[PDB]
Image (tube, helix red, strand yellow):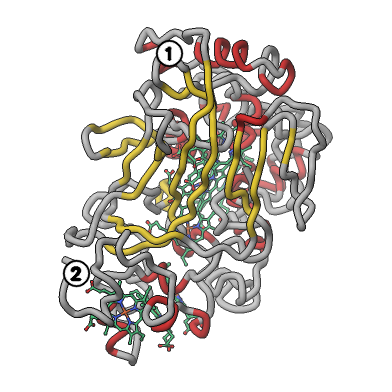
Amino acid sequence: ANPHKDVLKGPFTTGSEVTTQCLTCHEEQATDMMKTSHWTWELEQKLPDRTVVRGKKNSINNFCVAISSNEPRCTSCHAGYGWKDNTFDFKDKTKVDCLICHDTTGTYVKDPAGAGEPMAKLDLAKIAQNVGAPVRDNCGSCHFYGKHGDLDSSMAYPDKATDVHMDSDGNNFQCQNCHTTEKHQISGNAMGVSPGGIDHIGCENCHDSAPHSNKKLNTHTATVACQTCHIPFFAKNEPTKMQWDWSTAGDDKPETVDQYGKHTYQKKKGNFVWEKMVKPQYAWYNGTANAYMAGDKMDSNVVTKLTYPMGDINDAKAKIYPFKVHTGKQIYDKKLNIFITPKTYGKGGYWSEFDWNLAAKLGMEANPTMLEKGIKYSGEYDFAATEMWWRINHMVSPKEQALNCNDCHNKGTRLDWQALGYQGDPMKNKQGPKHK
Ligand code: HEC
Ligand code: HEC
Ligand code: HEC
Ligand code: HEC
Ligand code: HEC
Ligand code: HEC
Ligand code: HEC
Ligand code: HEC
């Protein structure tokens, strides 16, 4: 037994007061955790032409776009308390959130607009006393809401049909059963992070790399990622957003709904398309990814890929992997040719004032990178098309629903042979295209 139940009677009125207790004995864990991306929101990433500091802190996406000037809404999913703008003290140990991963009561909740602060009226003392090993639902406080359509609210206690590894009646894995954690470094590669292992966890430390009695299926694994055949669908239980058109935001037309009660229009955000039971898109992937970074020039007559997997048929490091792809339109500076990071949340933000010029001006004056590069909002904006790629790794289906020969070959359409660089279906056509 540990001392928790005896030492943490409180009263506690704030998160850091809780944390300041945890540190009388777990200063090491804070120090360790603070070295990681869960605390800094930064990752180094090797792009085709340059190494950058990406991570969430520096990323641009086609959903909410970017954290700067919006921090109080976004850092409800930071393992910290108080990150509300650019003055956040990343060296302050009393600001780590120790409860979000370790709460066992199921009541600990971070206020969705509170810059990481817990909701009002929690029994903090009680939460602190009951702290223990994370389960799926702790990771899921940030990982099941917003997007990746492969981790849903039902991954809290999913069935076999949803995920064979996490299946609470079967293998019942917690996330760290695969994402092994040492010194609060939670293992697992985000897309475009390496080194010479595309997947740090992948499928091959618990399965043989030739796991099939059918040898022809084993020969495919040099080219086709396990994830491709074994995750035939994501968003199995609940719709995910497939498109977000910001260009239409700001009108008082009716805020219409889906088959599934999801909004297809909202004044504050624009138009959406939702989909349930989604086939992935397939692409060559060798462990590296391209990314759009703040300040990059772009071209509005074309779709901009905000991220994209690298590799191709001639790339011996690349395999065909499955991806979720989200498309949209979003705001760009019509004079510089760059995407803008606008203020949507809070005072002057789009969501209260519905004025894109003001949201642009305020979001650009708050962005550290724009400032670093002397970039000023020009005063003119427009909307441009984008696509963004995320890896699909969860919801492995039972073996009976793996893609089989006829999903890809013969009348199968899973793979777009020519987009992948093949000369027709390789089974009809043993002449032109082979991986390596
Ligand atoms: C000393 C008075 C402690 C305070 C205050 C807190 N914790 Fe603790 N914790 C303490 C000990 C001696 C142990 C056992 C360490 C060992 O391995 O010998 C623990 C254990 C934990 C764990 C592991 C829980 C598990 O089920 O394995 C966690 C996750 C943990 N402690 C977290 C934690 C937090 C968040 C605290 C503030 C709320 C906290 N502890 C206070 C000693 C002490
Ligand atoms: C909210 C407070 C989170 C909780 C709770 C957990 N994670 Fe998380 N995770 C969060 C963010 C904002 C990010 C991106 C960090 C960045 O800037 O890069 C992540 C990332 C991951 C990753 C990807 C690797 C990485 O990006 O560095 C993994 C593999 C991951 N998270 C796993 C993970 C697990 C297993 C969790 C429970 C123990 C967990 N996370 C909690 C936000 C939050
Ligand atoms: C998720 C993003 C986490 C945050 C924030 C914190 N911890 Fe953690 N902790 C996390 C994991 C995935 C693990 C391993 C769990 C397992 O099942 O093996 C732990 C482990 C601990 C432990 C025991 C092991 C150790 O390193 O000593 C302790 C004592 C612990 N965690 C405490 C702790 C504290 C005090 C935190 C806030 C400052 C904290 N953890 C944050 C995941 C995450
Ligand atoms: C094995 C059976 C897994 C379980 C259980 C969970 N995850 Fe996972 N995850 C797994 C793999 C093979 C990968 C690819 C990365 C690798 O190094 O092999 C991932 C990846 C992630 C990521 C990164 C996704 C991305 O940004 O590209 C995250 C954020 C993530 N996983 C989170 C996560 C959570 C929250 C889980 C519990 C609900 C979880 N994973 C379980 C394998 C496995
Ligand atoms: C499609 C081209 C596949 C690739 C690539 C991989 N697998 Fe597969 N797998 C596929 C089928 C059609 C089936 C069902 C047929 C069967 O052998 O049952 C499977 C099955 C498995 C299983 C279950 C094996 C059994 O007990 O019968 C496992 C454990 C498994 N596959 C794992 C797996 C891994 C780890 C892969 C990458 C190394 C992999 N498969 C590739 C189709 C395809
Ligand atoms: C260990 C940490 C694992 C990792 C990482 C992955 N898999 Fe797994 N898998 C694991 C176990 C213990 C089991 C059950 C095996 C049994 O004896 O019943 C499985 C099961 C599968 C299956 C079979 C599902 C079924 O129909 O019963 C498949 C097809 C499978 N696993 C594939 C798979 C893939 C593609 C993974 C990477 C994303 C993966 N596994 C990771 C252990 C672990
Ligand atoms: C998609 C995810 C597939 C499934 C399911 C199956 N196959 Fe496949 N096939 C796929 C690719 C991407 C390739 C090219 C591999 C390469 O070397 O570049 C192939 C290739 C073949 C071939 C021609 C090569 C050969 O092995 O002689 C054959 C005859 C073939 N595939 C047959 C086959 C069968 C019988 C399958 C079911 C067990 C099967 N494939 C599944 C993609 C996919
Ligand atoms: C929890 C419910 C979240 C809230 C609220 C917000 N975000 Fe998030 N985001 C969350 C996680 C767990 C991750 C890591 C995903 C992984 O699989 O590795 C992220 C990541 C981002 C990124 C990086 C690129 C991407 O995956 O889209 C960006 C640019 C981003 N998030 C932006 C963002 C903004 C602007 C938010 C508030 C307005 C916001 N997020 C809230 C989880 C959660």
What amino acid is found at the position of numbered circle 1 in the picture?
Lys
| Residue 335 tag number | 1
Residue 43 visible, this angle: yes
Residue depicted at x 19% and y 80% = 430
- Residue at (43%, 50%) from the top-left corner? 186
Q: Position of residue 261 (x, y in %)?
A: 79, 52
In whole angstroms, how far apart are the C-alphas of marks 2 and 1?
44 Å
Q: Is mark 2 within 8 Å of ligand 7?
A: yes
Q: Residues within 10 Å of mark 2 (few under 14, many from 20)?
A: some
Numbered mark located on residue 433 in the image: 2
- Is disc 1 placed on a helix, strand or loop? loop
Nearer to me, 365 or 34:
365
- Residue kind at label 2, given as amino acid type: Pro
Residue at left offset 66%, top offset 61%: 156
Image x and y of residue 318, in percent = 25, 59
Asked whether 1 or 432 is in front, the reply is 432
Q: Establish if 128 lies above or below 92.
A: below
In this picture, residue 414 sits left or right of residue 25: left
Helix, strand or loop under label 2: loop
